[PDB]
Length: 242
Length: 242
Ligand SMILES: *C(=O)[C@@H]([C@@H]1NC(C(=O)O)=C(S[C@@H]2CN[C@H](C(=O)N(C)C)C2)[C@@H]1C)[C@@H](C)O
Ligand SMILES: *C(=O)[C@@H]([C@@H]1NC(C(=O)O)=C(S[C@@H]2CN[C@H](C(=O)N(C)C)C2)[C@@H]1C)[C@@H](C)O
Ligand SMILES: [Cl-]
Ligand SMILES: [Cl-]
Ligand SMILES: [Cl-]
Ligand SMILES: [Cl-]
Ligand SMILES: [Zn+2]
Image (cartoon, rainbow over all chains, first blue to last red; front, side, top):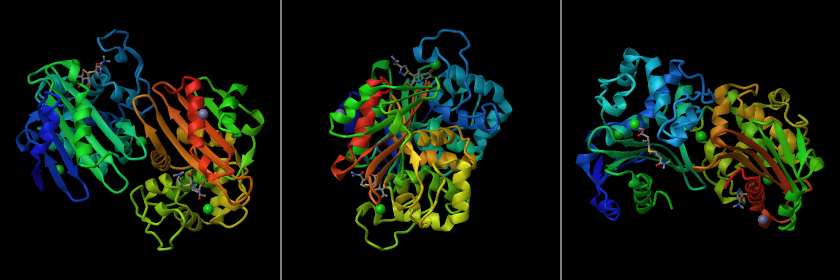
């Protein structure tokens, strides 16, 4: 069911990094990770919460479709890509928290809490601000729990409309070529130690789907690109992508 | 509305090719092409008919979803990738005609004809075999008419279910990265002269969509890569993609 491949640790060490990568082979129903312990340690989701947030906002009508413009509120913020108008697609690409904070406010505590339990998402705890608990509140999720959640979304098995799940998987589109499609979401948790980076999603092949969930210590922002780089090095090592 | 930029002809001549590239800027409602007349010249759609064929097959229940497997019929054909099982996604990726011919037969002449008129697709003429009319029958469509049809598909404004249009646009996914998304379908018409290549689809940017339809004379198969190459060289020249 679960095998620990410690050879993947070389990909972390070669970049002076530490963390965990979790892969799940959907065809054979087998999981693989370099660190079974960290694979099951729960962290703040941070921007990876964009996925369940978007599904709920769509299903409840808070967002009509992927085209609806979310106008800038005027306030100029630290990340330049947030200082512009956005829709559901671009909000996910640039992890525009103000947009998702508005999503959560209109959803409300009671509906957020019920939906996350319906999703079986993480520790299902929204303690803190209804609109920042995924950044500095009580919600925690592990890499293996991210896989379980992503597998339901892939199969349209989440307790929301099929349309909601199709739209969010469209927004998750990150890379595509003749060899594979990657649908994924990055995360960068800074408000509580340990500071970590996330990359969760899956790789679509012609005849299989490989889900992945990785997190790594991120004491500084210069190594953010290692989230994708280390994951792809493991994918390349396992001959899942060329 | 329309503007002719004859400088793009260099991209055809430098490859000893002739053809047309038609671009449509969705935000500005403006069109650009190297050849206004050939932009309106109608040809057999060939494999680009996979788009309306898939929409109809989905809307009528011929195809249940993008996962339904269509078993290889055992008949060994010249294109190896056709000699395997396929779903709606890999059927479009590998242009598997036998799959689409099975689609057409189950749709029927009467429903095929009614839907192409509802789609306002080309000259709406299905004369010939119900399972080969887009290959060697009477249907004809121009590059500008392809854009007209694709614009309706993008906006979910075709006379089919929204789910049907979302699934087909997922199957059209051809390339994606941090700069753009290309949803498109290639074509290669070899049954009736003149032999031509097609590439129709659109480029998704953060804040705009650039629809494109190109076709070119294809006397020899070694030029098939020029369908994408010439299109991307024009896209680069217009600073649409890096
Ligand atoms: C979500 O976790 C946070 C935001 N998400 C990300 C991320 O997933 O990378 C960032 S960092 C952002 C991405 N690249 C930008 C950059 O370095 N430059 C443009 C120079 C910054 C956000 C912090 C959310 C909690 O804020
Ligand atoms: C459709 O027009 C025909 C098929 N479509 C294509 C095509 O769009 O390329 C081919 S060629 C085949 C599939 N893609 C491969 C390719 O482009 N190269 C590797 C060069 C090989 C078919 C002929 C249909 C009517 O047969
Ligand atoms: Cl933040
Ligand atoms: Cl699992
Ligand atoms: Cl998609
Ligand atoms: Cl053929
Ligand atoms: Zn060239």
